[PDB]
Image 1 (cartoon, helix red, strand yellow):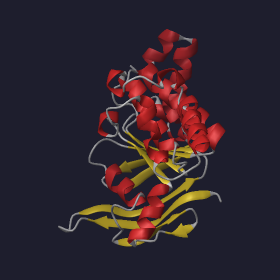
Image 2: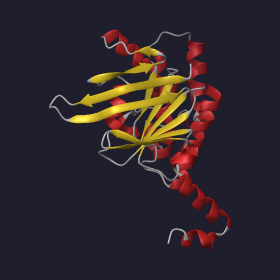
Image 3: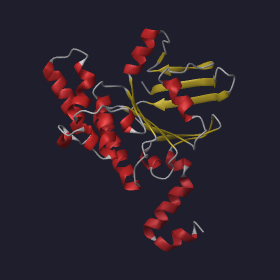
Image 4: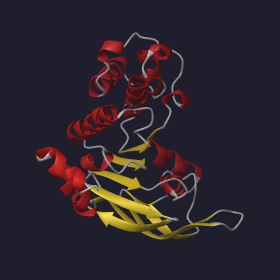
Length: 251
């Protein structure tokens, strides 16, 4: 019940023979916010595609929810119901319809009692802060609102894991902290595990319990962000108290 994903000695090579991930060991705790950090080309998408089964490891394995992944068609279908994906650009995920039609599209085809669809969708919209936009056309929303609609559409299925692909995209730093604090809050109320792929090492990690730094398809650092970015954190606190001394420490 500690780890929602354990990656054990995982290797991945593309079918052309390109070695993408090497001896990856990663233990992701249930009900924490974990981020996987690194610039492009580091292998974040390759890792995340293994998590939801679109790729299968060449060597080693992944335990999801304490159990091996079942790679049959049925097993993959089951695994993806447990795992919600929020895309970088919400346009890639949203329908042109009202916020309520889009978000409720998911429940509507699972044959639930209507009043259970009602609760699920309304709770989803409250939980993402977008009740007031229930009847607004998606095409009229800000990027930030759209992203909240994407998240809400995924909450409706009650996944166990929420995976966000670069959640800082299209957002100013205060935009970023808004979305991060929203995610920290929904975990408090839902117990959902949050996994983030990002290159942002400044804001995103202040909201994380755990962090993995990747380079050329290997983990090279890991742990509590307070400890991993111990030095950046000292600087941050200095700016907070003595604005000018902290810039001589960046000098």
